[PDB]
Structures are given as C-alpha cells and as structure tokens.
Amino acid sequence: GKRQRMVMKLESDKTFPIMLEGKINGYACVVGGKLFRPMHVEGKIDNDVLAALKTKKASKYDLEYADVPQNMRADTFKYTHEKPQGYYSWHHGAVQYENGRFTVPKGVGAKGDSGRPILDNQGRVVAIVLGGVNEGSRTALSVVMWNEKGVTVKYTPENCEQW
Amino acid sequence: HAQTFTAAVSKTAWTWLTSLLGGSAVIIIIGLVLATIVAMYVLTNQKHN
C-alpha cells in the first residue's frame, strides 16, 4: 500500500527510463555521482543531460558507469554496506534477504523491469536488480552489491534470464 | 671432415639466440603467473560478498 507510494516518492526525479522506439526496457540509477546502466538494455536516455556523456564499460560486472556533474551530486540516491537479513522494500512491494540472497515471490517479473534499485526502511540503496531466475514458488535475483572493503560483488544464481 | 648441423655457431650467437628465445618465454610465464594471482585475488576480494 504505502510502500509503493514511498518508492514512487523516493524514485520520482532520480530514476530515468530507457526508451527504445517508445518501449520502456530498463531504468538507470544515479547514485554517488555515478550513472549505473546495464549492457543488455539498449536505447536512448530520456534525460537530456545524462544522454550526452560517455559511459565506461564493464562487461564482467555487467555495468556501464559515468561521472555525474557536481550540480546534481546532491540529488542522488544514498548507498551503504551494512545490511542485516530480513525484509526490504522493492517497487513491486517487498523482497526477502536470506543467506545473502534476494528472493521475490512469484506473480511479478517480466522483461523491462531491469535496473530498479532495492531500498531499505531508511532510504538507502542496497542492491541493483539486474536479472531473475524462477525457483519453485519464490524467484531469486541476480544483482550487484557492495561490502565493507569496497569491492563490487555480483551475485548470480544458476540459469538466470536477463530482464 | 663432416658438416654437422649447428657446428659453427660461435658462442656469442648462442648467447644472442638464447636471450632472444628465452627472455620472451620468461616474460610470458611471469605474465601467466601474474594473471593467475590476479584471478585468485579477485576471488578472495569477492569472498566477503
């Protein structure tokens, strides 16, 4: 109920969709002065400022990143590495964090909702949704996250389908 | 006398052949060892996940 409204209030201005002949196939992320955007989502950036840049690539970690200018670094997402197990907020409701794995209940999940960040009860991004795999009743996510040392860890289960 | 293959190699040219043929192998095996150590260091730093 109110969780989706809080997601729409937090991700209103900072989330920009990716257009491809009128089709919405992905979402970029503006956090820490960086613009995260995946490889398989191909299209034009809806924002005029973020589209006229050059994104350095990382095909192993499946991420394109760039440098957000200084006049927009204050209006970004927050990020942290301290995460316990339990529940977190996602755009379609809740997501479970168990044994270092993000799980989403079924019914939701198609092609197009790639790049949506995972939020917490405070308002900090803990993961970035990149892919998903159907596991019985409860699907698992293939995402990226950080740690205490500062190494971007990409978690990928078996036989995932890119969204 | 008989014409042995590599009979007149004149040890200086053994040194030039051994340098130009062995230093390349040394550089490529230390590159492969460095690649293996970098892969293990990535798998160590991603362990904290």
Image (tube, helix red, strand yellow):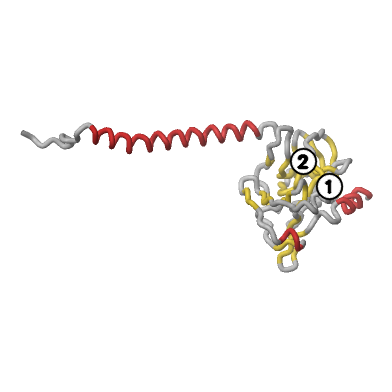
Q: Secondary structure at mark 2?
A: strand
Is residue B49 shown left or right of residue A10?
Answer: left
- Where is residue A127 shown, x and y percent of the image? 76, 43
Which residue is outermost to the bottom?
A: A21
Is residue A152 shown left or right of residue B9?
Answer: right
Residue in view at x 38 percent, y 38 percent? B24
Q: Are marks 1 and 2 in contact (CB under 8 Å)?
A: no
Which residue is outermost to the front?
A: A70
> Mark 1: which amino acid?
Trp
Is residue B14 shown left or right of residue A133?
Answer: left
Q: Residues within 10 Å of mark 2 (few under 14, many from 20)?
A: many
Residue in view at x 82 percent, y 54 percent? A14
- Where is residue A63 shown, x and y percent of the image? 67, 49
Q: Secondary structure at mark 1?
A: strand
> In which chain is the residue bearing label 2?
A
Question: Which disc number belongs to residue A157?
Answer: none
- Classify A129 as above or below B12: below
Question: Which disc number belongs to residue A90?
Answer: 1
Disc 1 and disc 2: Cα gap in Å?
Answer: 11 Å
- Where is residue A120 shown, x and y percent of the image? 85, 41
- Classify A2 as above or below A43: above
Q: In front here: A156 or A134?
A: A156
Which residue is outermost to the right?
A: A2
Would you name the residue on which mark 2 appears? Answer: A102
User: Which quadrant holds the C terminus of chain A?
Assistant: bottom right
> Mark 2: which amino acid?
Phe
Residue in view at x 76 percent, y 63 percent? A48
